[PDB]
Image 1: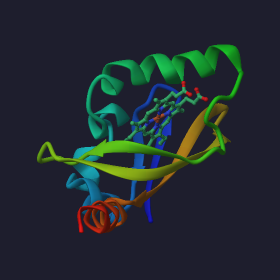
Image 2: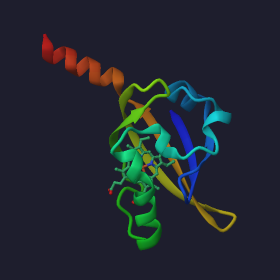
Image 3: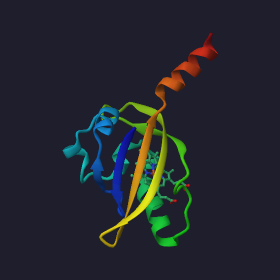
Image 4: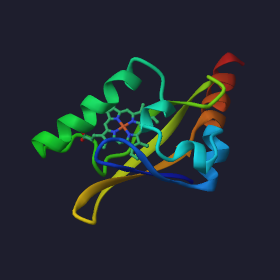
Length: 116
Ligand code: HEM
């Protein structure tokens, strides 16, 4: 699906091919950018606090729990996507791997069936 790996500060570490197609950023452009560039406000400005809250409390909220959210493409367009993150440790520091399943087609099919 699309895959993104970030470090404990929300910085993109790895960014898969399918992620590039989905979000519109190339791997080099994406890497080193904060994961919040992938979501609209008000979430964008808060994401760091979310990662910060968890880091500090050690109390999971959305770890291993998939939820539907609104993502943002490079061109400004937004779209619903299913997201699940796994926590992993490497080199002593924590990393988070997210799997994204695009849901636009589902949202359109559902909107359309409702309209008809
Ligand atoms: C691109 C669309 C995304 C949106 C809209 C989004 C939104 C959110 C929200 C609302 C929260 C906190 C929810 C709560 O308090 O229960 C959160 C937490 C978090 N997100 Fe995201 N996120 C996005 C993508 C990502 C990705 C791709 C990663 C991992 C590579 C990620 C990593 C995290 C982490 C580490 C937390 C903290 C977990 C916790 O507090 O339990 N997010 N996100």
